Length: 131
Length: 131
Ligand SMILES: [Zn+2]
Ligand SMILES: [Zn+2]
Image (cartoon, rainbow over all chains, first blue to last red; front, side, top):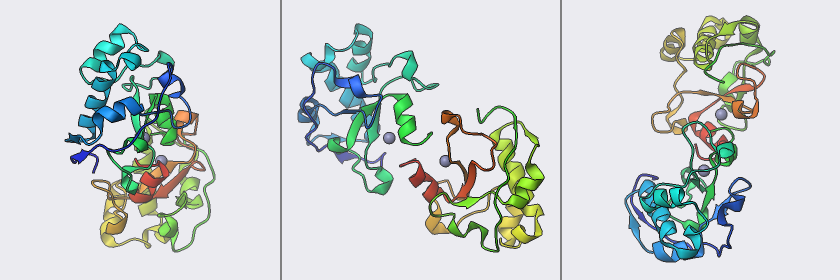
């Protein structure tokens, strides 16, 4: 399912000036309701496609982009996720990741933004108990 | 690291004639005490090496091997994991898997047989919340 096309849905949530502040704990940071407004009802080829588009919208949002360094904004401008602090990386996984709260393998929505959150590699791995 | 050498420790647990009975639920089936008796204190190059020798030991145990079909014994004889019933597979993961209760990423013993169990792919994916 993850690699099959779908339409984005979901409301997301309003975020403040420290959006990814809690990306290293619990379920991490929600999809901003501003980003969801831009992606909602849009068709994607695969989750990876959504992923790419998700970060591009982040670089286009005046309030969201300002919370990142130039280097991370440049990355997001081309669909690449922002790099985390060294403390939060794990091997080749060095940038913020998107997690599905309810696993796609368990009928979880692939493009349901209310089922998607932003987490650090380190936290994502702990969420999946080591993977 | 699961890719670095180490010595197997742990006592394992007694089993009956239905060893992999609960491989599809909870933490699955434990490492047979009989298998741990043979592997304890031995050195392995990597967890993969342990995995192969673990299945080899199973094929060598009369009580355990007799619980599998000829085709599955053939696989373990050469260090390969036995195939599961179709309902328990997931994509290319079609054979029983070893799961570390406490993850290596969390200082869990890589070769601690009391931290290792046998689970179907479907169940293992569920334990890792989606992967
Ligand atoms: Zn996840
Ligand atoms: Zn596992």
